[PDB]
Image 1 (cartoon, rainbow, N blue to C red):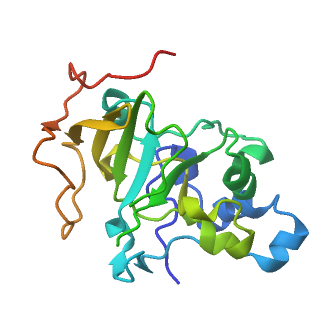
Image 2 (image 1 turned 60 degrees about the vertical axis):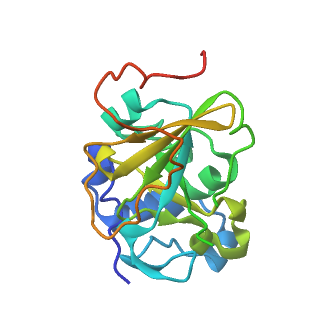
Length: 221
């Protein structure tokens, strides 16, 4: 199969690497027992989506729950916690990331369940954003580990080196579980043929700009 691999990455050194090298970084620390049963599976360029419709990888609707507001995320994209040029093996391991979610080179997303989405424990408390992502490549965690996948309900797609701002279409701003606004990213590279953004008519849709007065809402640190 063919894949776009790490094309979405924001970290330039990860973005410059051959797919075989990034693959090695991701799998090298897997236990032998896991290596026997598992193979690293990148999302193919053509995939079967959760509604059994066959789509281009960029047309699979991914979401990321994130406490950080659009004034950061639409400006920078999703930069992973670890960006350094010589990361520890712990920081590049897909299995440890999938299992424990410790500081790493990956940005987590989840697949839209088209027939709903996995929701984190405290998504209905404080200020949280559901960012809508249409990105090339990335690693399919469930296909990689099959029944050894530690949290299969997360339907996780991991992006080593993060996700450029051009692949983020929109963001739902929730305050204590209730939607306040739908942010539109003006720098989204539209691949065409996408469904319109999901919306109630009650919810205002706001075109984002840098340092938008309402675009920095977040929890106290």
